[PDB]
Length: 21
Length: 29
Image (cartoon, rainbow over all chains, first blue to last red; front, side, top):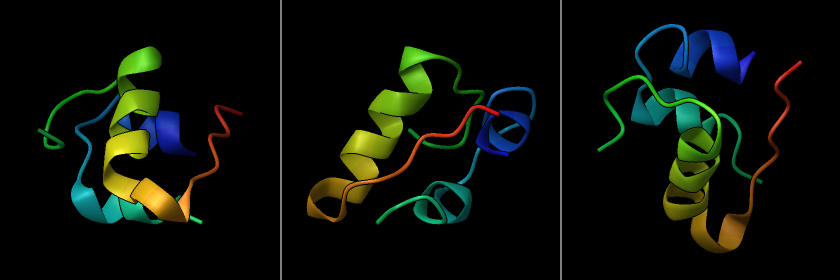
């Protein structure tokens, strides 16, 4: 999930854009 | 500003800025 990829580990623009609509 | 640990409201704020008019879904699981 987003928390594991961006909060407990360092986020990235690629990862954020995975969750855009 | 996206290459860091983003938690809670900080993460939701980053999604809001990045996704813009596309919107986003936030699923903390």
